[PDB]
Image (tube, coloured by chain):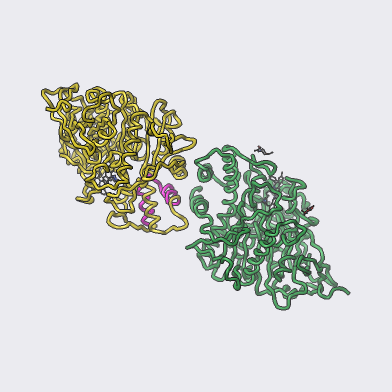
Chain colours: A yellow, B green
């Protein structure tokens, strides 16, 4: 028995496993239960703390993936399969993982907590791209990641009911955060320096913890990559979650009031619920997800828009950013004319039609406005332009402009904000060239995977990943991503509403740019709401 | 006796002209030739009638009366304004034209250029210094003709459907002068089978209206439109709106409005200056770049809106040169936008910018104005008073001239026309408007007419060569339908404007540079999105 691999937490003893990182050993504790299995009558319910266990709990393997839809568009293609469950599906999935340095840190170390994405309908903390091994080994970080319930299991809501109050997957995350406060010191983590970070839905989740008072005492800094709590896909109104839950129930034969409806849903096999998950969306669309956090008046006291507009963010530090082609990869999930297996050169007609699908809530006038803005009037019918514009429309509406308004609002209201745009395309990428640097493809680099020589990343990419791991952990450590030794430029400046400085993350040294897609986001954040607003 | 080269006969009767001095040598000039019966008394508001023949030799050595007309007094003594003001007596008796020809008159029939002045349809005169045809005549061998046409109420006050005030009579004055060139210009050595209309601002819009009005089409062969178009927000009005303004003007001088004969009769008894004193008071909103009495869509001269006629017209044979100056809007701003003056830098606040946009785009709803403001804001420096000043100028320039021109070039080119397009980017060294106004509306004319060739005017040597270059493009175009020089291989070429390639040229001190899209992103906002708003 290795004494470094034995830990006592509140609930009992645990045995981890020494894993190999290229620079040396790390201690990993995988599959640690943080809640009572949310099964049977606990489906749709807020999670309860895990009861104490006897003996030594085996924490050497990843635990089950939360029940979710599995992608079937491109079977056995790396670019999709890399996001698919890599363990057994089960409703019994409330476990987290901890990577620490080996030997365990001598003095308390800043803690990073990862929250995965997947549109609140998918994801898992066990995917190879979320491997905490590298960050633990090179930067000496204590890295934590939890599973949280997704799809119906995490977010089906009958608002105001006792037995489907909504947002429970966000409560799973909050419970993992509390678990960290109570327990991370036993691993040599510092519960007094916790940085949340996440991508896509994970980034929106981090956003939600910023916006929810009970979460605030559980972290000190935040990183939101390619996602925000504001914007068109991350939340729904109470009225709208009730409609979808009700509709899903109708779809699976329930009922033959809220209590009855939820009791009958509870009798249904998990796959029955996933079978009809997609059919509750109000419009033909892309970048919209059936079961997401609901504006409940509880976890979320008002809309994320109202909350960001009026919040006090004085002692908060935030790192936010986007990748170069946020919307490209989404296009093949519903826009006629797009495929990964050809160059996807579209007609003008295919563009107008794709806009109604990229901006599913847009009126004729509003979609006309989108079209007229994104057209290159010098080359109005050029298929390459039209394709890139369609991708641009989706990236901007869903990620880049929501990010830009989050950054401005936080900065204006006392927070310390650092922003980036990530522009390096992975040499190993399996999606076609026209998709560029798609949603999700920075993660790989932040987590330090290019340092594994067996993964065939170029030398330049390894150095690049070393730089990114240093920014992220510098940020966790201090709230400032800059290397406090060196001494030479260019320094990453804070983002502000005046100057609007952000940096390009790519193979070249940091470049400072101003204005995060400024004219275009003004279109989305200031004009379009007004459209659309008073009419209709 | 008497210079034998200055005696000519027209339909008409005998004319005596004057030998004038141009820098390169003598030109012939026949100034103040009457082409209509004086449109006075029972004839105010009425279409013009042909001038009745005279006896003896009519003296044609001095400019005749300017049409009666508001005189600018915003900046008294200031050359930037006084250069546009009347330079002869104001009279309703003003329907006269001018002819410049080489001296001695040309051997073989020469291409004719007919100038039509601007001034918002409320002002202008063919006798102004900047419209002097002596240089084009002497240097290019051109026959140049310019006419006075009635402006303001006299030219354009309309009670659509009536006998007594049908509207568009100023346009009809221009047509009559065109008919006169057909019958008579051969007497001066002009070629009636090669007549090119050119004009700037309202002159340009006028030219466009002759293109769109069938009876005018047989009277010219080619057309040049400088900083103006028949389509756009200011060049025309509906029948309903012209009726409203005429009626209101009537009231103000009242003349209590009750059929149309009684009302026009009463308006007819009013003194000219009195109509001018109230002209401005009929505008539906506080505005700039809007004029009270302009061409009306009558279903006669203009069979439908200029927009409908350009969208559906067939322009197979037509050759047009079209263009704009770098700063179309700047000088309009001192005539009504709070915050702007010629005597300071006119740095403005964001509030003053929003307030200006409502005045510059007076027909706009709150939704449309906010669209304008958001489009023109520099979101990186949204409070910068220099940028706000410049945005306000572009808002006015784009809405009133650049985008209506771009729309025009696009439609004509799509429907058979050969179109050539320019942006004029040189600031006269002699300009007296402040530096912030850039190259304002009107300030290419001076160069097209070759004024810099007069050494007494203090232009630079390069300005002299530049004016020479321009006179040469314009008269090549008149001559051949192509502004390019056929012999001159090395000089850069001026390609036609097409929908596919949207090419146009920079006119400045440097050799021609070919650019693409005038000025596509922004004009898509005005011509494609904004109407669809708005509405
Ligand atoms: N016939 C059906 C039945 C059920 C579902 C179906 C289709 C679809 C669907 C599949 C193809 C085309 C249209 C629709 N869908 C739609 C899923 C597709 C939408 C997301 C795809 C996507 C694309 N990207 C950008 C590129 N990178 C990623 C991904 C994926 N996941 C992630 C997760 C985190 C970060 C990045 C990332 C997964 C897919 C591929 C790329 N992110 N997500 C379902 C969804 C449900 N919630 C429930 C059931 C079903
Ligand atoms: N208090 C009064 C009473 C009556 C009139 C008044 C004001 C005004 C006015 C004056 C100052 C400020 C606001 C309003 N106006 C306003 C007219 C002012 C708008 C025209 C000024 C202008 C400015 N530009 C651009 C610069 N270049 C030119 C000009 C002018 N003319 C020309 C003609 C062709 C090409 C260029 C050019 C004349 C003036 C200055 C510059 N073009 N035109 C009136 C108009 C009428 N039709 C009748 C009466 C009155
Ligand atoms: C310029 O003068 C005008 C009118 O006299 C005035 O309203 C404006 O405030 C002045 N602008 C500046 C920058 O001083
Ligand atoms: C031109 O130049 C001279 C200075 O050499 C000046 O005295 C004269 O008045 C000027 N004339 C004009 C029209 O500006």
Q: Position of residue B128 (x, y in %)?
A: 75, 58
Res. B98 image quadrant: bottom right
Q: Position of residue A522 (x, y in %)?
A: 46, 42
Q: Does the image show residue A464?
A: yes
* Depicted A381 relative to depicted B245: above or below: below
Front residue of A418/B52: it is: A418
The range drawn in magenta is A349-372
Q: Position of residue A63 (x, y in %)?
A: 16, 34
Magenta stretch encompasses residue A363: yes
* Depicted A281 relative to depicted A187: above or below: below
How many numbered discs?
A: 0
* Depicted B469 relative to depicted A321: above or below: below
Q: Position of residue B212 (x, y in %)?
A: 59, 64
Q: Residue at x 27, y 56 (%)?
A: A341
The quarter in which the C terminus of chain A is drawn is top left
Magenta stretch encompasses residue B78: no
Front residue of A247/A222: it is: A222
| Left or right: where B272 falls relative to A148 | right
Q: Does the image show residue A284?
A: no
């Amino acid at each position: 028995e290795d004494p470094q691999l034995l830990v006592r937490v509140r609930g009992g003893q645990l045995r981890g496993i020494r894993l190999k990182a290229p620079g040396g050993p790390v201690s990993a504790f995988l599959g640690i239960p943080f809640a009572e299995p949310p099964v049977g009558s606990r489906r749709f319910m807020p999670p309860e703390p895990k009861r104490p266990w006897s003996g030594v709990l085996d924490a050497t393997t990843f635990q089950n993936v939360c029940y979710q839809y599995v992608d079937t568009l491109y079977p056995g293609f790396e670019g999709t399969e890399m996001w698919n469950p890599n363990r057994e599906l089960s409703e019994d999935c409330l476990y987290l993982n901890v990577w620490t340095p080996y030997p365990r840190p001598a003095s308390p170390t800043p803690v990073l907590i990862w929250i995965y994405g997947g549109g609140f309908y998918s994801g898992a903390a066990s995917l190879d791209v979320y491997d905490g091994r590298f960050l633990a080994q090179v930067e000496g970080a204590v890295l934590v990641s939890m599973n949280y319930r997704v799809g119906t299991f995490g977010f089906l809501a009958l608002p105001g009911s006792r037995e489907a109050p909504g947002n429970v997957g966000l409560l799973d995350q909050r419970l993992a955060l509390q678990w960290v406060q109570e327990n991370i010191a036993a691993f040599g983590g510092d519960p007094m320096s916790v940085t949340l970070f996440g991508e896509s839905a994970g980034a929106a989740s981090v956003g939600m913890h910023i916006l929810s008072l009970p979460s605030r005492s559980l972290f000190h800094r935040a990183v939101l990559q390619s996602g925000t709590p504001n914007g068109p896909w991350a939340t729904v109104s109470a009225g709208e979650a009730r409609r979808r839950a009700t509709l899903l129930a109708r779809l699976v034969g329930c009922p033959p009031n809220d209590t009855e409806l939820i009791a009958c849903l509870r009798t249904r096999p998990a796959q029955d619920l996933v079978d009809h998950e997609w059919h509750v969306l109000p419009q033909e669309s892309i970048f919209r997800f059936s079961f997401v956090p609901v504006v409940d008046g509880d976890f979320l006291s008002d809309t994320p828009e109202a909350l960001i507009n009026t919040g006090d963010f004085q002692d908060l530090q935030v790192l936010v950013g986007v990748v170069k082609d946020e919307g490209s990869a989404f296009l093949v999930y519903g826009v006629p004319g797009f495929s990964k297996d050809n160059e996807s050169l579209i007609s003008r007609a295919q563009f107008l039609a794709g806009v109604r699908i990229g901006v599913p809530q847009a009126s004729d006038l509003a979609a006309e406005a989108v079209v007229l803005h994104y057209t290159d009037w010098l080359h109005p019918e050029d298929p390459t332009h039209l394709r890139d514009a369609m991708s641009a429309v989706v990236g901007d509406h869903n990620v880049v402009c929501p990010v830009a308004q989050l950054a401005g609002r936080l900065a204006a209201q006392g927070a310390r904000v650092y922003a980036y745009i990530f522009e390096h395309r992975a040499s190993t990428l399996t999606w076609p060239l026209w998709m560029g640097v798609p949603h999700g493809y920075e993660i790989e680099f932040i987590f330090g995977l290019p340092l594994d020589p067996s993964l065939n990343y170029t030398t330049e990419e390894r150095i690049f990943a070393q730089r990114l791991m240093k920014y992220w952990t510098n940020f966790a450590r201090t709230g400032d991503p800059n290397d406090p030794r060196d001494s030479k430029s260019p320094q990453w400046p804070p983002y502000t509403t005046a100057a609007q400085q952000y940096v390009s993350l790519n193979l070249k040294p940091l470049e400072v740019r101003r204005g995060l897609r400024a004219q275009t986001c003004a279109f989305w954040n200031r004009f379009l709401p007004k459209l659309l607003s008073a009419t209709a």
